[PDB]
Image: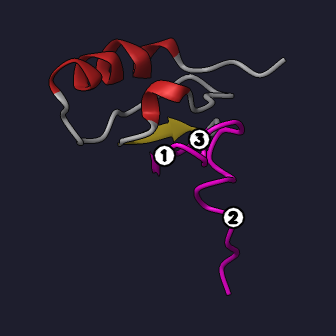
Amino acid sequence: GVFVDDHLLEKVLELNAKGEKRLIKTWSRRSTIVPEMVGHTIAVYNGKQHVPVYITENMVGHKLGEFAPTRTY
């Protein structure tokens, strides 16, 4: 169904090897989070913007609405 940016993994799996807690940028379209993002702020490309969502062990599963479920107000 949904796709998980493989370009974020190429950088997040590297952060899971040493323990780096940085952010991974993405530029696909329907980019979704993964289990390897439980300690990274990956700016998933929602189609037009890279939302650096710091995923924990219970935020992944969507794409960015689980880390940014807030409106302008």
Taking the spot 68% from the left edge, 28% from the top edge, the residue there is: 30
Magenta region: which residues? Answer: 48-73
Mark nearer the N terminus (2 vs 3): 3
Q: Which residue is mark 3?
A: 48
Q: Is residue 9 inside the magenta stretch?
A: no
Q: Position of residue 6 (x, y in %)?
A: 50, 12
Answer left or right for 26 relative to 24: right
Snapshot quadrant of residue 33: top right
Per the model, the C-alpha gap separating discs 1 and 3 is 20 Å
Disc on res. 55: 1
**Residue that appears at 61% across and 28% down:** 31
> Mark 2 to mark 3: distance in Å?
17 Å
Q: Are marks 2 and 3 in contact (CB under 8 Å)?
A: no
Whole-angstrom CA distance, mark 1 to mark 2, is: 13 Å
Check disc 3 and give the amino acid type: Lys
Residue 58 drawn in magenta: yes
Q: Amino acid at mark 1?
A: Ile
In the foreground, 13 or 27:
13
Q: Mark 2 sits on what residue?
A: 69
- Rendering coords of residue 41 (x, y %): 38, 45
The disc label shown at residue 41, or none: none
- Mark 1 in CB contact with mark 3 (< 8 angstroms): no
Of badges 1 and 2, nearer the viewer stands 1
Give the image's coloring scheme: secondary structure
